[PDB]
Picture 1 (cartoon, rainbow, N blue to C red):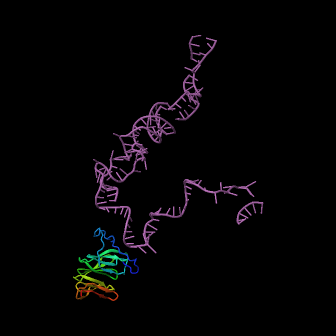
Picture 2 (tube, protein in one colour; picture 1 turned 180 degrees about the vertical axis):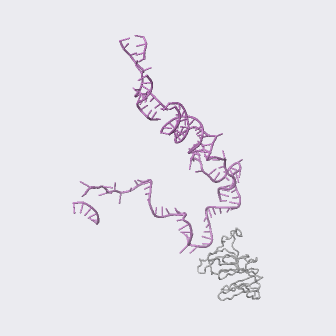
Picture 3 (cartoon, rainbow, N blue to C red; picture 1 turned 30 degrees about the horizontal axis):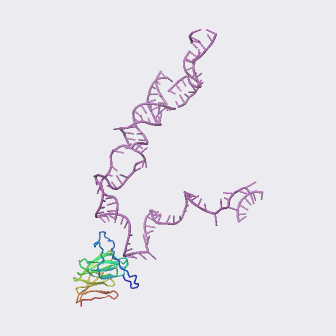
Length: 188
RNA sequence: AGGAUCAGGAAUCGUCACUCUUUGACUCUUCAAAAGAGCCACUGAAUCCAACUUGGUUGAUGAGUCCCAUAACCUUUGUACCCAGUGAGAAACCGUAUGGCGCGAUGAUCUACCCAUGGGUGGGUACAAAUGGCAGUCUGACAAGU
């Protein structure tokens, strides 16, 4: 967590798991290794420090861990794909209540940042998802996939609104919340 | 002339310890919670299960010996008492001119009921005694160290 203000407030984040809220013990080597290297990042500071607000898509893991930005430490919930694919892109809700997780098999899970519970598991893509977003009002959510599809869904509602077919498969998705556009890189 | 405000009456010490009491601080701590200058990291310690080790039913641990089972409190059977004390009252002559145990204070005299001063029953008080009551002969599987 580098600080562009002051070079000494730059601090390395913790990787120390919270003691698991279930009680049955967690899965990992006792030689505790670091988390595998990350391919995607996601953070909204709307409700910071009341729960987790950093989602990181680690290398070749079926889930993606959550972190408190304020506590400089990986938080309590890990967020799965639930279709046995890799997490290949993540983004979070601007209300700080949802993290969106896009599989390599196309399933987009909407986990909650409250209890680590899932909300909905969308299935539109049969290729990999490669970039997700939500609009700034948390009304209409987009996703770009490795199928060449950009899917328009509502978030309050549950209907697939639109389905734009682009030419090459779509590698990434950047959204502008203030102006409701969204950009994408493709293989073209 | 008697009393109370601002000569009829002991109190001039360069301290050493000791003890006691007193209150205050204090690490804490119950009433009883509640609030937490918050997060990381490093490093230390401690505890608890798993683990392993050593010892252990040839007995690990747990344990009110002494407050006396060596008893207390009774209960029944053999004795000592008293409603030790009482204290002046108990029985009628004399070996060979003469001599005495012939009582007794220095002790004579006795040891709530019925029966003509013969015997005992009843209660308190004490002890000896119980193979009598009250009053029915321990646990047994982990422990301990990292």
